[PDB]
Image: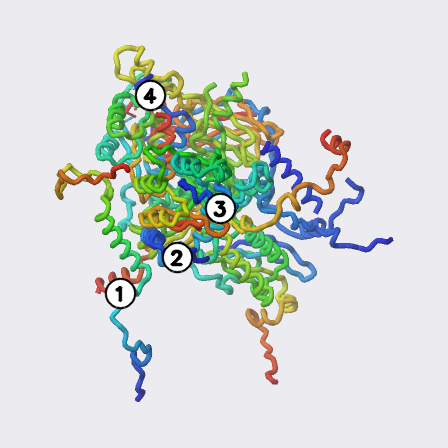
Amino acid sequence: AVTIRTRKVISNPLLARKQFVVDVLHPNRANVSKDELREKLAEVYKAEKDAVSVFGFRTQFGGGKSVGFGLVYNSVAEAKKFEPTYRLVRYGLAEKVEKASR
Amino acid sequence: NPADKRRRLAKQYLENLKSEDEYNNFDAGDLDKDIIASRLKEDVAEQQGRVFRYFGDKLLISEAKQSFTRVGENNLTCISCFQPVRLFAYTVSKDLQLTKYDITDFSKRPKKLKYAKGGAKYIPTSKHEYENTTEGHYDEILTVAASPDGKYVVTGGRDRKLIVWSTESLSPVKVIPTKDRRGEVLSLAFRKNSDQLYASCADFKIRTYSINQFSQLEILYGHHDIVEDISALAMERCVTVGARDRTAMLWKIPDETRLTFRGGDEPQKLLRRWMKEPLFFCEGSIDVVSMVDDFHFITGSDNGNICLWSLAKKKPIFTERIAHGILPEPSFNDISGETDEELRKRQLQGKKLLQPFWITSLYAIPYSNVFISGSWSGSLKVWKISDNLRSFELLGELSGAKGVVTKIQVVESGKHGKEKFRILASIAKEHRLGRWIANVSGARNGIYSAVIDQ
Amino acid sequence: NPKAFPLADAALTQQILDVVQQAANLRQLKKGANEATKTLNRGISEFIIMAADCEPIEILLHLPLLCEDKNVPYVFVPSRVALGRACGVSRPVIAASITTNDASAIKTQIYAVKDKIETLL
Amino acid sequence: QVLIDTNFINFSIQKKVDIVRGMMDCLLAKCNPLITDCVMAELEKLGPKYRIALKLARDPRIKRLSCSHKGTYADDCLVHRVLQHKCYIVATNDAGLKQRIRKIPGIPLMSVGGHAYVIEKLPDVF
Amino acid sequence: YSTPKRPYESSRLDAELKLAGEFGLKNKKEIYRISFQLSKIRRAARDLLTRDEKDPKRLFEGNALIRRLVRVGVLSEDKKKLDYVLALKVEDFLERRLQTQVYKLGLAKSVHHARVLITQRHIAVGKQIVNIPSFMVRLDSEKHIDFAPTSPFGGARPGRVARRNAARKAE
Amino acid sequence: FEDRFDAREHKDRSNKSRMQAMEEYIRESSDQPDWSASIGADIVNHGRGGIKSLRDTEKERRVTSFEEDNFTRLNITNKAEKRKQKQRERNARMNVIGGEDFGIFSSKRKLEDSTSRRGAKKTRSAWDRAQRRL
Amino acid sequence: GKRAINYQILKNKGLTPKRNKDNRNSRVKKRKKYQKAQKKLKSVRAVYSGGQSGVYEGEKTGIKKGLTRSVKFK
RNA sequence: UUGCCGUUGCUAUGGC
Ligand SMILES: [Zn+2]
């Protein structure tokens, strides 16, 4: 059973966003399991599962803890506006390939 | 003078480091971080709460309604209580039984509701340290802890298990073993208004759990003897005390760092301090804690000390040397075996082998001005801490509790200026860890409740 | 001079009880009066701690004669209850013994306590 | 603790090494230097040319033993009292005494070489 | 590290024989490394003795040196003098390593059993599994050397040999 | 003549004089505790590195504070890492023994010259030293 | 149809003497030359083995009334 | 008001 801890929750009205640091705790598990972590984050906060996102995962030595960077949006459309395209390729729906020449 | 030169050179050093009040006094980085402080959320859990309940001299002391409800369980060990924002209490014994009480009928003795008794039936069929997932206690339940929300009680003892029982039925919902051979739990404390438990296990270890997720958060290491007591408040700090290493540590649990506080009273300098014009001495083992607020706490020792410690001083702020008396010396008909009283008196060596009572229970009411100490002197003591927070002082005594006090905690009633509390104290005739206790002087295994007023 | 003569004061008592607790964790402590006299006549003992307040006193005063015979330091702690609590068992003990070991991780501490109680004695 | 003899003292003064400070920065340990009464007898018998060496051997930091034999043969006295006990460093520069001492086992040997003292049969010098 | 002056004298060979046999060392490089940095330590303490009392260097670097030597654990709490740093030596330093300490605490039956426990990761001081044998445990990490909870000598699930034998005996 | 804006003289240096012996004495006589870690959490590569030194855990705490503070991972920037990580870990395994660095005892740097013996409060008058005492 | 190479052409250990299993590990060699050394030490000195084990049976090896193994002075 | 047992109160105590 994974365990979740949010810390230092601030609000960004300019980016319509709420951001925090994510202490993810998995004793006798491998690692963070980021999609399941987005599920757990989207249910501890409000619904917006295609508007919650995590990117900066570092597991400490020997496992157990990992610190990530969590940012949760309202309004999935403006989340699609404000998130970068590589994270949208990683998690959500966007896929535009670069033209392979030279 | 070498220490004078050390102090002088350290002062010059700090002056030089400063080298490398006006009308304008504003610093850009400080005010930017204060803008981020105005931007952030969650001013809820992390209150550095000071002492906001100044009521020590206010309430009455000497005429409490003291009911010592004796129960038929050998050597009660712990007491857990609960208040929402009807009140239940919990006791547990060395006879492997948990017992639920109702306590909310305030003017009278508590009411038994439900047993939950483990026994020899719950010994595991493996003797293997990770299939310890049975549903009951087979050895020596040492501590209970009620949830701050009241869905669960969680208990554990020398069978190295944490069994979490439901409140409404006293049923084991989940079993979490501590996965090693010496992993006996000795103290449990929820952080206040939460679902997070801090257990202190004799592996020099502190385990943390989230109870409603059935998960373990963090194991944190660092004491040097068994972590005999634990204490927590609404902050994610914690305060533990290991027994014989004579240090109390407090843990930033997310950072996994600590502040250590050693003791350090010596009878040489103490008897010289009295010699400038006396039966007091060094320290055995720091035993019990309770975090009074988020800047101070208090420790109960093995030589009867009660000490008051701040968050900003390694050495303690205040001591109180003898807090429950010195024990009655062993009789001349039970020391020597000679015939004459002169030689049987010579076998007492005067005052050299008088040992003090050791405080085996201490409870600070959270953020309040008053704490309660208990041992087998027969009389609980009530002390209030002065409003400048650099001393405490004995208010009164509660003399209706014959036996060892294995647990003290209080139950609140009344509003902001008019209040009444019932002090529960588990009374046994045997210390909560080993036996060690002779001269059982009229003790009974009961619950000493007192109703204090105003 | 009482019968339980070379008693320790409070600082030496706590030094003794701390190394007793560590030897009990390291399986280097034989606790109890007849186990102590067994290990004393066997010769595997570095110093013996007797508690000077048990209900008779000659019950352990038999041991100073044995220690004197075999030249072993002996010291009197003034609490059998604290001695048992340091020994780590759930009862008071009246005598305990630190057995000799050279694959022992507390040999310096045991030797320092031996020197202190021998200059006392 | 280091037993000195006369040519070690003479070579110390000829190379301008202090006795206890040269011993300390040779061994990186605290040294107790010992002048036996036969080494002292030999320094006194060396005459009034060696007054500087004699009153540098007269030093309160250099402790001194009391040999109990007839005659003042320091090489015999040093060899006997070192092969009796094996708790001694021998500081010497005699070739014959150096060969005797390094033939008897377990005895470290110190000697003035260059501008500081050297030590050979002590296996823990760094 | 650095090689000694006369590396092949018979006292040095019997010295290294006793050290490597009594502490389970693999070669001469363990002794030479720990003795090289001990040489630096007490070559510094020699200069701290050759300067005088009430020298600032002596006062501050002396109590700094003896306090961090006490916290490494090679020096006891009561000898807070600076000549004990000169009396210090090499096996006082390699009694502090984790192989020696595992054997002395009795989790292993010899120093070689301790070395293979450490390199097979059954030993964890504090939180982290330590896996190299020459670790130099400190006076606060002295009492949390225990079996790792990820290991069958702790309380964990038994290894591949035990479970394969159990399966084949179940067949 | 005229003024010229000098950030090197109103910049916080505080490091020319930061000596570890003085800082250790201040930590000894500090009378407030020191934020030490739970004891296993500060060793680094299962013991393949050291424990970690006090300056290294201070620098690690600073990096994680800046890290969480503006949401950015630091990187593997080649020139700075080939200098600092390799030279730092090699002098760590040289001089850091058991979580304690002994490099300073092997280093010529005068204590009283730079970090003690005050320069502003030099008191070069009998009257000024008399008023500085009284 | 793949004529694979074999061990003597692969590792090329041409014509070596017979060597030692204890030499294949640097640690086990010093474990077994220290056991040899401390078995030789019982021959030269007399080693304190740990005192009297059980009942004193006797000297078990002989008593010489002519030999005196004590260091005379000068 | 309890594992027994006694005084019990018409509720409090004290021996294992
Ligand atoms: Zn002579």
The amino acid pointed to by label 3 is: Asp
Q: Nearer the viewer, residue B309 or C66?
A: C66
* Residue hosting label 3: D25
C84 sits left or right of B62 in the view: left
Could you tell me which secondary element the residue under label 3 belongs to? Answer: helix
Could you tell me which secondary element the residue under label 1 belongs to? Answer: loop
Using the rendered view, name the quadrant where residue A74 is placed. bottom right
Q: Are marks 2 and 4 on the same chain?
A: no
C-alpha separation, residue under disc 2 versus residue under disc 3: 20 Å
Characterize the local packing of mark 1: few (<14), some (14-19) or many (20 or more) Cα atoms within 10 angstroms. few
- Please say if the residues under marks 2 and 4 sit with CB atoms less than 8 Å apart: no
Work out whether D120 lies above or below B331.
below
The circle on residue C5 is 4
Q: Nearer the viewer, residue A58 or D105?
A: D105
- Please say if the residues under marks 4 and 1 sit with CB atoms less than 8 Å apart: no
The amino acid pointed to by label 4 is: Phe
The circle on residue E7 is 2
* Residue hosting label 1: G21
Q: What residue is rendered at 33% in x and 57% in y?
A: E116
Labels in figure, total: 4
The amino acid pointed to by label 2 is: Pro
Is label 1 or label 2 in front?
Answer: 2
Is label 2 or label 4 in front?
Answer: 2
Q: Nearer the viewer, residue E48 or E65?
A: E48
Using the rendered view, name the quadrant where residue D30 is placed. top left
**Quadrant holding ligand 1?**
top left
Could you tell me which secondary element the residue under label 2 belongs to? Answer: loop
C-alpha separation, residue under disc 3 versus residue under disc 1: 45 Å
